Every structure is written in C-alpha cells, then in structure tokens.
Image (tube, helix red, strand yellow):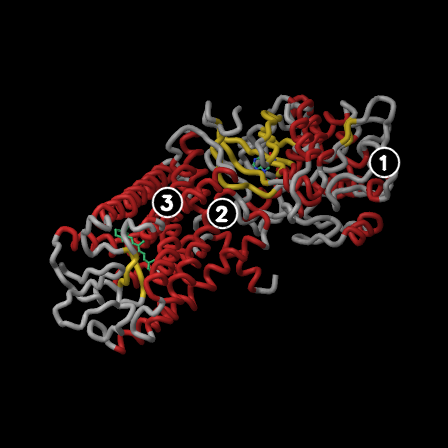
C-alpha cells in the first residue's frame, strides 16, 4: 505494498509533471517526520508542480513548547535566499498545523543519496564529494556574510536537486547576530553536529558551523559519523564527551588533502579550527581539497558531480522510514497557543 | 407466501408441516438439525477468536506510534471498531442461542441484536467505501488539488455511522422489523416478504438499491480508476523497474479488494432480489444462513486486507512483537 501504491501516486504525478488557499494542495505520502510535524510531498493547484511541505504540528508544538523555535525558522528562511540556500515559497497555517512550503530539490537529500547510489557503497567517490563540499562552503559563506551563525549542518539538511547542485536547508536552529556582537552563547543544533563551545554553553563565532562542516564531510565520504559508528547515536552526556575528547580516525578512503582538511575542522580548539581564522571564509578555500574547484565556475553553476540523480524519478525517504514524536497526551490548547498560531501566520 | 407471517417473526420456511410456530418459543429442529447447530456454534466461535485479536492490533499499533494518527487512519480505526460491534452484538449472541437451537432472547432481544449487528456491518460496509474514496481522491487525482485534513476524516467517520443508522434504526420504529434469519439463532432484517402494512416492500427496495447497488457502483468506480491511473503511471515511468512491479501488484491487490466487498454483501442482495422477483419460492432457512456466514467472516478478512497488507503497519507490528 500500500506504501508502494502511495509511492506510485507520487510517481503518477511526477510522470505527468515531467511530460494559496489552505485546501489547495494535493497531498501524497510523507517523506519523513521532520523536526516537529511531518514533511510530506504536495502539489500546486495552478501549475501542477511538486513541493515538500514541512508541517509543524500544533500538538507537537504545544508539547515541546516550541513556539519560539518556529517563529525563528520562519523569519530567517523568509529573508535568506541565494543559489546555495533553499528558498521558502509559502508560510500559511491550517487549524491543525503550521505549514512551510519550500522550493524544489527533487534529487533527494545527501543522507538518502549515500544509500541510493548503492547501500553497499560507503559514501561518495572523492571528486563527487569535493564538488558537493564546494557548494556547501558557498552556502555557509553566504550565511556568515549576513552575520548568521547556523550552529548546525548535517547531511540530511544538504539537499540535492536533479542536476546535482546542492543547497543547505533549515535555518530554524540558527541565530542572526547583529553587527555589535560577533559571538553569542547558547545550545542549538542537533547533537553530534555541535561544536565543543555549544555543548559547554560558551561564547562562539562562525567556527562552530565549520565544525559541523567537518562532521558532514566525514560522513559524506565514509558513511558514518565521526563521533559514533553508523546507525548509532549515544546519550547526550556521552556524545558530549566524544565531541570534546575523541580524536577522530581517518580511513585511507581519503586522499592526504581530505585527511588534512577533516583534521582541521574536527579540531576542538576553535582558534586552530580552519574556517574563519583571520576573518576569512576564503582562507578555507585555499586548502588543497579545493584544487578541482574554481570559484568563478562554482558560482556560475558550471561544476557538476559524477553521479547526477534522475530528473524523472523522485528520491527521498518513504512513509515507513519515518519517525514519530509526542502529539498531545490529553492536553487541550490554551488561548495563548491560538494567539501564537495567529501571530505566526503572515 | 413462502414463509410464515407473524407480528414480530417471519420464519422463511412455509407452514405446511404443521409445526412452524414462533422461533422465540419453539426450538428449531423441524427445519434444522443438532449437528448443524454444532457447526454454527463452531463457526461463530472461530470468528470471535480470529476477529478480536486482528481488530485489537489495528487500534493498538496506532496508540504506540504517534505518527500513524493521520487523516487517512481515522477510517481504519473506524473499520476495526465496526467489526468489533459485529463480534459482540452478533457473533456472541448467535453462539449462545445456537446451543438452544433457537433464539432465546425474544422479540426485544431480536431487535437489540439485529440493531448492533446491522450497525456494525453497515459501518464496516461504508468504511470500505470511504477508504476507497480517499484512495481515489489521493491517487487518481480526479479534481484539482485539495488538502485532506483531520477534520474531514472525522466527518467521513461520522457519515458512515449516519448511513448505518439509516438502515439499523427503521426496523425499531415499525418500518420493517427484525426477525430471525439463518437457522433462527441470529436476527436480520425481514426481506423475505412484501408487506405494505409493516412497510417491508418499500424497505427491501431501499436496502437493495441504497445499501448494495450504490456501494457496488462506488467500489467499481474507485478501484477501476486506481488501476487505470497506476497503469498510466507505469507507462510514464518505464525507466523505473519498481513501477512495473507496482502495476502488476496493484492489479492483484485490487482484485482481492473488489472480491472482498462482493463476497460479503452480494449473497444478501442476490437472495433478496430472487425472492422479490419470484415471490412464492420457498427454500429452507439453511439457504438463508449462507449470506450470514460470508458477511460475518468479513470481520476477519477486511482488516487483513486493509491493514496487514500495508508495509508500514507490518514493520511497526513486527517491532512491537519483537520486544519494542
Ligand atoms: N525540508 C525539505 O525541504 C525537505 C525535507 N525532505 C525529506 O523530509 C525528511 C524530514 O525532514 C528529510 O530528512 C528529507 O528526507 C525533503 N525531501 C525532498 N525534497 C525536499 N525539499 C525535502
Ligand atoms: C438485507 C439486505 C442487505 C443487507 C443486509 C445486512 C447488512 C445484513 C447483516 C447481517 C449481519 C451483520 C449478520 C450477522 C443488502 C446487502 C443491502 C442487500 C439487500 C438486502
């Protein structure tokens, strides 16, 4: 399968496609259970084009008291648009969930794409990884130039389009700093993709985003996290100890340039962590890893990877690869909740 | 006629052997046999033993996985509940009664049991219809883009209930009546005679049209569309091996699904129609137990088809069974 039937309906829409109102989008199978609510495929009434819609369920919002986090994600994504960061197309609400409808990236996400090349292929070949890394770097740089610390980044938040141009996505765990503070403290991001500074609740700058880049790249090539083996994630306290203490081992899958690059990013001393040392995001680009890359050609979209996903076959996790989270345990919405939901809606 | 008229009973066997009385006061053994009752009791026991675990699982798995509670799952929960109405209203009663060899809860009991059984079976019937509708809307895309939300789902659940009440409630206010069917140990709706004074004739026409023919058309429409859509999809995606498997698989599944609706309600419709067209054709009440057997067994096969054969549900159930 019935799950295959739901997938088949998606395929049916895609085949036709290849060849607001809140009751104005045809719903297909979910593609995951996101940060809050579900993130499902959906379709335009007026153009017949496919989009993912990250829904943040009202119930799940009340449970975590995630009202601040929602508003942040809205404002940041709404403002931030480039060629290496995804655009937001709509922000409306229903009576059950808040909706973000975001722009096409039908090539699946890098985390999926690791396994879609072949599940027994651990990550990507070196040239292919280098291309994606370069594109990710440009996205990070663009955030930093607007004075935004992301505090996160992970493979599943690096999405591929059908041409194999990648973009970073989700800016809901980010903070935009003003020009006057170059550092902030806090705990933000997904554990196991967070730098030492964040976990310890200390001041940090743009460095932490580059720590996350290191974690991402390491997983991109080797198909496992640096701080735990694949298909694992230990408790927060232990994970925190791993991030702070554990010297990451580097397989021979890597070239010398990639080994060295990974070492620089996975350094637990921010001062020695390449990324924004001497206030340069272009200092990072000088590393031998980026030998294949020319900045002008990268910016012009003239660089492509070896594996390019099909432009007629959809890619992403199905409806049985999903997660789940607490919808209300007998807890009915307060007036305050309703007022936030109204306020959120634009 | 071809039965025996009464004021609250209609034995579908003619009185001509001079032993046909009220089936609430006389033990049936002049149109049934003790062995047939043992088989009846066995069959009903089986259906309880299978039906209750199957329907319990459907509700259970949803309670322990948050994410399964979605608009499309309301109807599935409803189906499981509907089936359970048939189990505790119908099956258990019939099991008790069969061992006396007649219906021992009397005319009032007959109305009660008949109400719960009809209510159950009709919510189930219409559940299968709504489920097909939801699938048709989502997959076949018949009209331009519309969102499907929780509120709509709830309305859908309520609607099946209303249609079921529209059938189960009339015989309680004297627009038809509940009277023993089968071996006279279960009560169904009277349909074995036209009888204007009790409004049987008009009701039988209403039942046959609204509660069989209408459903039958809808079932064929929805699933016909679905197979059409999936074949088309496969044609537009012959660059994916998966889709080719899917078209064959969808055709197989659809045949199973269509057959399951047919087996359950076609016997009742068929028998009722035949008696109506050829009024004066007497047959034994054992002939009338045949539709009941098929219908009651749908409490087992409907949730097997519509729950168990979904990949997602399987995985979750396996996880739960293997200590998780
Ligand atoms: N937020 C987005 O834009 C998307 C999230 N997913 C999937 O939904 C999952 C849960 O967020 C992710 O891990 C992806 O598999 C997507 N899959 C395909 N296209 C997209 N635009 C997204
Ligand atoms: C009378 C009748 C119908 C429905 C019968 C039902 C719903 C019987 C349920 C019996 C049970 C649940 C016994 C146990 C149909 C199919 C509309 C066709 C027309 C005749």
Percent of width and height locating residue A277: 85, 31
**What crowding class fits label 1: few (fewer than 14 Cα within 10 Å), some (14-19), or many (20 or more)?**
some
**What crowding class fits label 3: few (fewer than 14 Cα within 10 Å), some (14-19), or many (20 or more)?**
some
| Residue B136 seen by the camera | yes
To which residue does mark 2 refer?
A: B73
Which chain does the numbered disc 1 sit on? A
- Quadrant of the picture in which ligand 2 is shown: bottom left
In depth, the one of A226 and A91 nearer the eye is A91
Residue B38, compared with residue B206, is above or below; it is: below
To which residue does mark 3 refer?
A: B163
**What crowding class fits label 2: few (fewer than 14 Cα within 10 Å), some (14-19), or many (20 or more)?**
some
Percent of width and height locating residue B62: 54, 53
- In-image side of A327 versus B272 (left or right): right
In depth, the one of A253 and A226 nearer the eye is A226
Q: Residue at x 46, y 63 (%)?
A: B52
Q: Which mark is residue A185?
A: 1
Residue B260, compared with residue B233, is above or below; it is: below
């Amino acid at each position: 399968l019935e799950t295959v039937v739901a997938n088949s309906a998606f395929i049916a829409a895609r085949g036709s496609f290849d060849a607001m109102g809140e009751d104005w989008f045809l719903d297909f199978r979910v593609l995951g259970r996101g940060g809050f609510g579900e993130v499902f495929a959906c379709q335009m009434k007026a153009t017949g084009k496919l989009y993912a819609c990250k829904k943040l369920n009202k119930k799940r919002l009340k449970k975590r008291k995630g009202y601040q986090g929602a508003m942040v994600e809205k404002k940041i994504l709404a403002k931030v648009h480039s060629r290496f960061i995804v655009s937001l197309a709509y922000a409306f609400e229903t009576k059950t969930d808040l909706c973000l409808v975001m722009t096409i990236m039908n090539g699946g996400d890098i985390r999926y794409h690791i396994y879609n090349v072949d599940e027994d292929n651990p990550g990507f070949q070196e040239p292919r990884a280098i291309f994606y890394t370069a594109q990710i770097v440009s996205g990070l740089e663009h955030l930093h130039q607007r004075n935004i610390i992301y505090r996160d980044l992970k493979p599943e938040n690096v999405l591929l389009d059908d041409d194999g141009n990648v973009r970073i996505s989700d800016l809901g765990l980010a903070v935009e700093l003003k020009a006057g503070q170059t550092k902030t403290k806090g705990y933000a991001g997904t554990p196991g993709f967070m730098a030492p500074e964040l976990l310890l609740g200390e001041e940090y700058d743009f460095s932490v985003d580059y720590f996350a880049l290191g974690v991402t790249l390491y997983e991109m090539i080797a198909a496992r996290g640096p701080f735990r083996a694949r298909g694992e994630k230990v408790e927060n306290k232990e994970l925190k100890q791993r991030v702070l203490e554990q010297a990451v081992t580097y397989p021979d899958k890597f070239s010398p340039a990639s080994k060295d690059f990974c070492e620089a990013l996975l350094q637990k001393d921010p001062e020695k962590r390449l990324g924004f040392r001497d206030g340069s995001c272009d200092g990072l680009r000088t590393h031998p890893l980026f030998r294949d890359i020319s900045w002008r050609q990268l910016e012009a979209g003239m660089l492509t990877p070896p594996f390019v996903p099909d432009s007629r076959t959809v890619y992403a996790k199905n409806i049985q690869d999903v997660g789940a989270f607490e919808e209300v345990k007998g807890v009915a919405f307060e007036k305050a909740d309703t007022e936030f939901f109204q306020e959120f809606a634009s | 006629m071809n039965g025996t008229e009464g004021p609250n009973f209609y034995v579908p066997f003619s009185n001509k052997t001079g032993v046909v009385r009220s089936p609430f006061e006389a033990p049936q053994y002049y149109l049934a046999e003790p062995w047939q009752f043992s088989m009846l009791a066995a069959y009903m026991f089986l259906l309880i033993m299978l039906g209750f675990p199957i329907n319990f699982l459907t509700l259970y798995v949803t309670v322990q996985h948050k994410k399964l509670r979605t608009p499309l799952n309301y109807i599935l929960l409803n189906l499981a509940v509907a089936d359970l109405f048939m189990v505790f209203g119908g099956f258990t009663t019939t099991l008790y009664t069969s061992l006396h060899g007649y219906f021992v809860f009397g005319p009032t009991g007959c109305n009660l049991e008949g109400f719960f059984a009809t209510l159950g079976g009709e919510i189930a019937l219409w559940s299968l219809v709504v489920l097909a509708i939801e699938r048709y809307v989502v997959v076949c895309k018949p009209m331009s883009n519309f969102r499907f939300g929780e509120n709509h789902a709830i309305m859908g659940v309520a609607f099946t209930w209303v249609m079921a009440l529209a059938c189960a409630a009339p015989p309680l206010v004297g627009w038809s009546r509940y009277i023993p069917e089968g071996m006279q140990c279960s009560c169904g709706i009277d349909y074995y005679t036209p009888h204007e004074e009790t409004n049987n004739e008009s009701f039988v026409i209403y039942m046959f049209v609204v509660h069989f023919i209408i459903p039958l058309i809808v079932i064929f429409f929805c699933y016909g569309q679905l197979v059409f859509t999936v074949k088309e999809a496969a044609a537009q995606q012959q660059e994916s091996a998966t889709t080719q498997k899917a078209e064959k698989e969808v055709t197989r599944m659809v045949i199973i699904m269509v057959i399951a609706f047919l087996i359950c309600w076609l016997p009742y419709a068929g028998v009722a129609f035949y008696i109506f067209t050829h009024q004066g054709s007497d047959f034994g009440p054992i002939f009338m137990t045949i539709p009941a057997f098929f219908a009651k067994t749908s409490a087992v096969y409907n949730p097997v088809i519509y729950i168990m054969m979904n990949k997602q549900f399987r995985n979750c159930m396996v996880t739960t069974l293997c200590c998780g």
